[PDB]
Length: 55
RNA sequence: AGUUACUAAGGGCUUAUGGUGGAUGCCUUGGCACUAAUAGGCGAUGAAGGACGUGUUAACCUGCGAUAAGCUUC
Ligand SMILES: [Mg+2]
Ligand SMILES: [Mg+2]
Image (cartoon, rainbow, N blue to C red; front, side):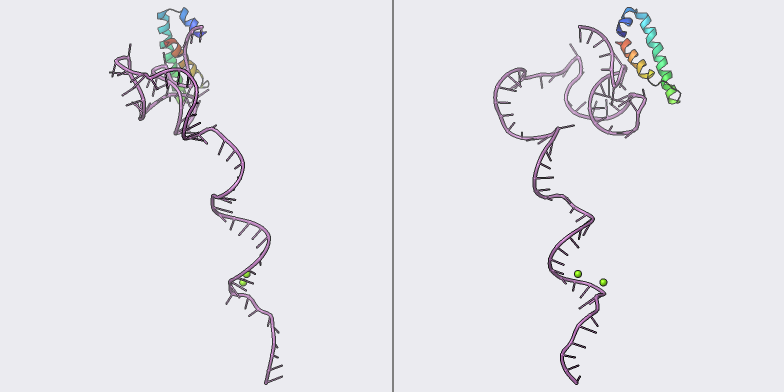
């Protein structure tokens, strides 16, 4: 399902996606370390989407 | 003058009860010995075995490997 959407995308757009999700993942981990993450599941979703884009 | 019971500090016997203890009985996500087939290897495209790390999840165990409690396809 998600893999189909990324397959339609080109390569350059994918590397933009991976860097943006990397940045967001760092922010989520920092906010969690400050006790300011209301939604604690976005860390897992970011990592899975990151792993899928890598695949 | 004569023959005399009561005493139980404590102990003994019988029976009943309580406590420590896990023997006997029943059972088992565990072992043992084989039968009928399959198969008889893995590794420089990095092995067997380990260390470390990975959670929204204290530690331990299991899974996994910076794509880290999972990724794609049929
Ligand atoms: Mg007495
Ligand atoms: Mg007595």
